[PDB]
Amino acid sequence: KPSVMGQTANASKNLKKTEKSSEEEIMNNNISSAQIKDNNQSTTKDNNANKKEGSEGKDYFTAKDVAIILHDLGYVATKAEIEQMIWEVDENLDNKVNSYEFNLMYRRCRYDKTGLEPRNLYNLVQFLMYL
Image 1: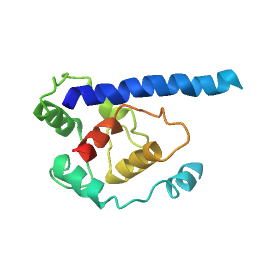
Image 2: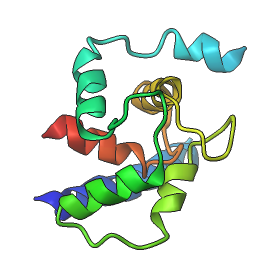
Image 3: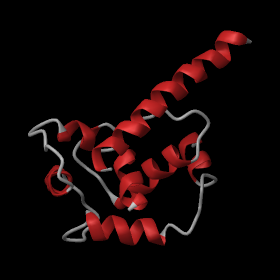
Image 4: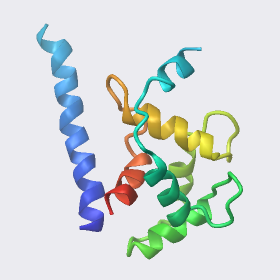
């Protein structure tokens, strides 16, 4: 169920955000929230993220690796759109994806109030942790 799952999470979010709107229809901040967000045994996520994405292993992650992972997943690698998947969460330096940036994104998207932040890149992290 490789593509249909990225479609599930998508459609669930599409309904979730409609209900989030319904809620209002009826009736150092970054780090201070990061530290408290989920601190589960993320050695699974770290070892898995390096095992599936981190090839060279120097705190650096590009679009070529995500493109080849997408193609290996039997997915139709859109030639240039994967750049947006790399970019949507890049906040310090455009074309800089650090392991610390994985921590920040993973964590802000894992434990938060609403979500909606990208809803579209860490779905792949959810997939790799899923299988």
